[PDB]
Image (cartoon, rainbow, N blue to C red; front, top):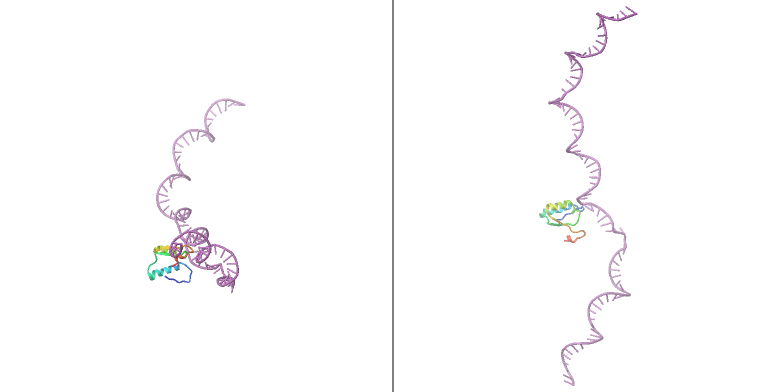
Length: 69
DNA sequence: CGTTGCGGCAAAGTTATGGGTAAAGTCACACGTAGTCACCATAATGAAATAAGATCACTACTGGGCAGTACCAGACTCGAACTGATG
């Protein structure tokens, strides 16, 4: 899923990419890595991942190879 | 006896490695790197509201006393009269 918005990183971002994911494809990941953003340390994204049963994985700060691909 | 192959010995030959010295390269000085949302818990009021509390008003139930009435004598006081001593 690809999303484009003028705003800085904020949940809306996340609702969106995941909406399209669950829209044109069908479901959603199983383990979703996501750096140590704020959009990911928020309550909304974690609650949504819990609701849809996605294992949330977090790379350590300043390390980029963990999401290198 | 002479010749031929083989092996020890000791320079000599070839790589390698850590030093020194001039000399070809290399690259920044050219105004600039810090700067900006996103993030969710805690204090912190101010308002919203409380749940109980406070008082009014009415209804019914039950203690219960005061101004007044009434009798039966006992007892002190005194009009009115009786009666004796007297100067």
